Length: 164
Image (cartoon, rainbow, N blue to C red; front, side, top):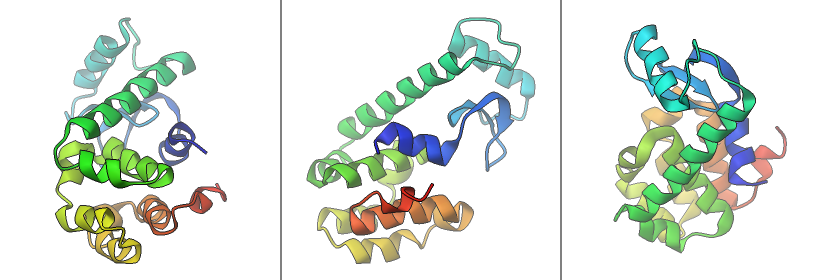
């Protein structure tokens, strides 16, 4: 299992603009287009991102391209963030995947906000961190995904996704 397959399980693939769990305009593999309520705003963003007139629809190839960019950008973001980098650096391969997943879903700033949890992960207090992370809007809003991530930080294995 790798970060790409893991994200693909959590996000799914959609080749037409769609609304995410929060109601925002998205395409492909969880690529947020705009937080704007306008489908038009969304189509514009889309064409700008792809480099063609897409008319709200992309190909598999285009989706996978956006995906490669977003994962790359999530990683680089962690590495540049002063709160995130040290945690990432302290973690094993599986757990690092979990932080990338979180970053991809909620942005650098958002994960950087989980101060107590980050500290616990740094200290390798697995179970305590699992309990802390569950006390969040994140967990109450997308519980199955948050539990997968949380289980992964907990055990340091891919079991939660070996199901799926």
